[PDB]
Length: 111
Ligand SMILES: CNC(=O)c1cc(C(=O)N[C@H]2CC[C@H](O)CC2)c([C@@H](C)c2ccccc2)o1
Image (tube, rainbow, N blue to C red; front, side, top):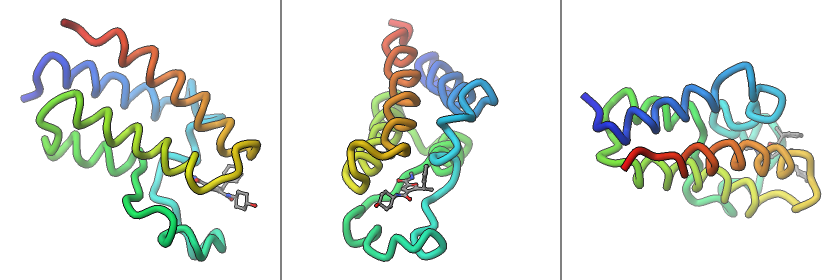
């Protein structure tokens, strides 16, 4: 069972993972494979990795007790991208676009 607010969160999560946003959402689908990408400093800079597959697992496992905890993980995922990457990089542009999708729909949370 989810609260009404956690159903809204699950709706947002489904949208973030949908083909509609795939052009800019794809970097956030799975955990960053730092070694495979040659980003050998990634885990020295990012102490708390997060991605949409981990958010999905936590939602499915009823890990999130409220909307605020869900939103904290989604924003942690974007913050990690903004911390690690140069601000003019394509991946940061993709993060900004997916975060715009997230923030505008999260704002429509039922009272
Ligand atoms: C959550 N993903 C990331 O933070 C991330 C970082 C990266 C990545 O390569 N970062 C660069 C930034 C510039 C620096 O000079 C070298 C490392 C990528 C990959 C996969 C990506 C995604 C999109 C476009 C292009 C490269 O993904």
